[PDB]
Image (tube, rainbow, N blue to C red):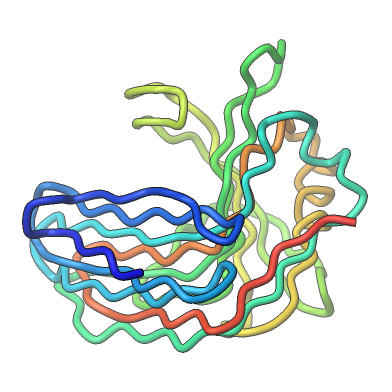
Length: 219
């Protein structure tokens, strides 16, 4: 139930109570840990306020890349967390829903890494976008190119899709399927749903994300 990164091992991933877990630290320094709770719950801590320090901890539901992400009639995520950045060496962090749309076998469809960002500190990705209303709240949506390693392998150029919550928070209900529908309404390509995860990420920062409630489901 506790996993550590930064002194010997820089990654752990597995499954427990039907929910994935993953923790990762780059080889640029720092340390971190994830303590599992029941279900999908977890506490993550990181100390990576060093140059190019880079940390992530996430848990979620694997969907098996079986069908178009928008074919699921309803996907819900309920979460509650304490989330704090305690150091920043020109750094940042975010708490978000996270996953991929797999395009393997899909002609004309991009590979996508997606983020529904509920809270952030110091910096968050941004680009020319559109405001939309989901779950009673304003989110800015946009997409951008990224070049880097991928669920399928090493450096390729793929797409990232973003919804960024305008009023930061650390608990509530997210209608994940509604975000997917808004992205689709822009004419963005939607591949097969790989996962739906709650993700804490740190760049050149230190902090804690104590996720005491996390439920992901479809109907």
